[PDB]
Picture 1: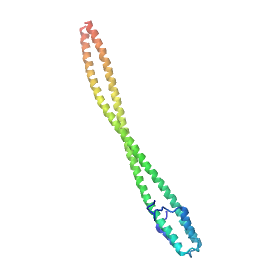
Picture 2: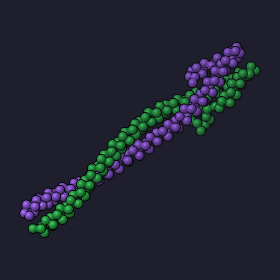
Picture 3: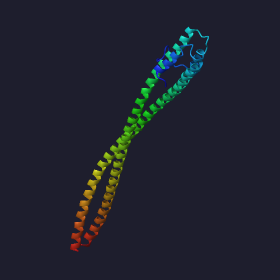
Picture 4: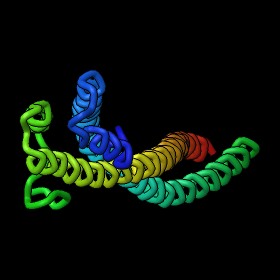
Length: 112
Length: 122
């Protein structure tokens, strides 16, 4: 888009009514094209901004999903860790009884 | 209700800008109405460039804001996958230990019956 000082210069060249009609129409073309392109680019950058805001919110919502999924996973892992410890104790106890009964069987086998 | 412009008007519409351009085309136009029309274009353009610059800087901040949000989302999703994989591993080891305990329970009864039979043989 034209800078305000360049727009002003076109305005001041158009201030002379003695200006040649070829440069008069040329300057009028400059303002016309510049303004049409300006409104187009303005509208373009406007919708770009509204979409970028939706882009932010979607990213934040994908972050809300991810952080909550992680937290649930961490809690479930801790719960299973507690349950695993209990089961390890049961297996250790059952292993010791297996050894005890293995020893008892050998004694019985030697006595028969 | 634009507050960048004179009055509550917003930017000139392309047809209104064009009408002013066609008023400056008249060689009979009064020099006072020529200066008036040039003033219209001047005020409108300065006010429009002001609002344009503001929405311009707004865009760069949303762009940095997007990437920071997406990268904090990349992190969060990576954290979640790490957590879920650890949860899966804990589930597998818990399943293995539950299988081991069931096996040992079956073995205990088997040996209990064996002991009884052997003891009855004494």
